[PDB]
Length: 336
Length: 11
Image (cartoon, rainbow over all chains, first blue to last red; front, side):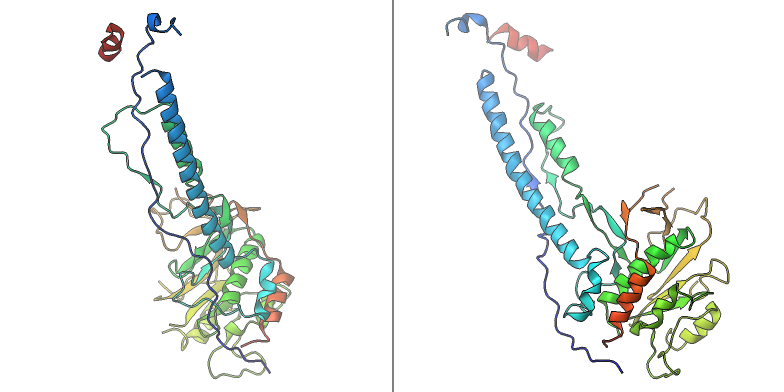
C-alpha cells in the first residue's frame, strides 16, 4: 500500500550566534568653553568634540553592521525552519519531510504567521555612570539604534505546542479553521507519524471540510485495521474520540482538534504532553490573568490576536485553504 | 581659567 521512509539526518541551517553584543556608552557631554573671541579674531574647541563624535558614529556604524548580521542569521534560520505555507507541498517528496527531531531546537513548534520576533541577541550597553549627562548626538543615535534594531521585522514566529497543552481559538466559523488547518499542516509536514499523532472531533467531518484528514498517516494507532483507514481518529463525539484514544492516552505526542464549541470541550484533560485544540464561540471577558500555557487566540482577517487584559502577536496570518491541505495530505499519504 | 567656564559650571 504505502512506501517506506528512511530517516536520514537533518540538514543544518546556519545557526544564530546567540551571544551578548555589547555597545560602548556614548561620551560624557564635554563642556566646550565659548571661544573668547580675542583668540578667535586672530585666525578644547568644537573641532575636538566633533572629531570624537565622528569616531563614536563610526563605532556605531560598525556595531549596527554586526547587529544587522545577527538579525540576518536569525531570519535565515527562521525561514529555513518555518517556510511560507505554499513551499511545504514540495517538501514531502524530497529528503526533508520527517526531519524535526526532538533534539533540534525546533520541535512541536508551529508557524502561525509573520510578525516582530524580538531578536534573541542581547544588545546590552555597559552604561555604568550615575546619570552623567551624555553627548546629545551620540546618545540620540544609540537610542535610535537600540529601539528599531532590537526588533526584527516580519519574520516567521512559532506557536510552540509542546508547552501550551490547550489551543482554544475563537473567532469566525471557518476563518479560524484556516489558521487551524495551516499550522496543523505545518505540524504534520515536519514530524514523524511515530513522533506525533493527530485527532479530530467534528460534526460534519466528511463533507469537503476536515475530511482532508482522511489521508493523514498521523491519525493511526498501532495494530488496528478498521477496513480502509488505519484508525481514523476523526469522529463526531468527543467522548467517543476519548474512548478511541483511551489506549493511546495514558512519548508519542498528540494534537487533538475539536470543532464543536459545545459538546464537552476539554473533556480529555482537566494531560502530561497531550495538547488539545478547540474552537469556542465567544471570548471570556475577565479571565483571571491567563497562564503562559493555554492561551486565547481570535482570528481576524489577517491577525491572530492573543488575550492579555490587545497584543496582536501575529501581524499577517497564514491561512491555508481546504484543497491546499488536501494536496498536502495527498502527497503525504504515499510515504511512511 | 575663564570666568565663563566657571559660570557654566556653577549653572
